[PDB]
Length: 213
Ligand SMILES: Nc1ncnc2c1ncn2[C@@H]1O[C@H](C[C@@H](N)CC[C@H](N)C(=O)O)[C@@H](O)[C@H]1O
Ligand SMILES: Cc1ccc(C(=O)c2cc(O)c(O)c([N+](=O)[O-])c2)cc1
Ligand SMILES: [Mg+2]
Image (cartoon, rainbow, N blue to C red; front, side):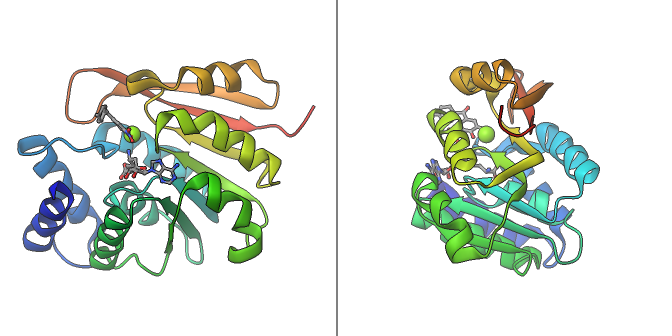
């Protein structure tokens, strides 16, 4: 699989325990060989900036894929900070674990195998989560708005919870974007960038939760 290819390429070309080289090898391969839906370096640098700004103790990632953004975020996590990541594809999830294992980041991260819509309502229950400091939305684009409503519904957001959504321009999340921008429950900021491994304009939206009406 494409994802085996990427994992193996990292195992051979990256340095173990070094999250940077992991990222850089993942990027080199997808730039030069096989495009992959990693958030990539350009948008990733904006993620980095947002993570460094808010120093979340608990991040929820929707869509882990090969672990590129999990590695990207986890390396910036403070001591004791936890990243939780949801990945419904068991193959992808096994790849993500291997990547995070290789990055020495496996202790900061918990991989949840399942659909976000299924896993979100059990977060407090099974995973000892009160509320989320930060959420990275990067799974199927039709799930951004529904999983936001679900996260809100399940009491997983607090005042100042940061939602950071990838691909709000391409492939695009128009309903989500319309919703957070229009709602008083969310203060939004758009970060214009580029689709990973091409000249297509894409962006990240930061949507900070304000609490209910
Ligand atoms: N509803 C869902 N629940 C959990 N995982 C999902 C869901 N929909 C899509 N996914 C996974 O989300 C991933 C989407 C990727 N763009 C994630 C990339 C990853 N955030 C990265 O930049 O490294 C795929 O690997 C999907 O299998
Ligand atoms: C068939 C197809 C079409 C468009 C893309 C695509 O561009 C893309 C980019 C992402 O950052 C991303 O997160 C996802 N995703 O999870 O669906 C898709 C990728 C594949
Ligand atoms: Mg994406």
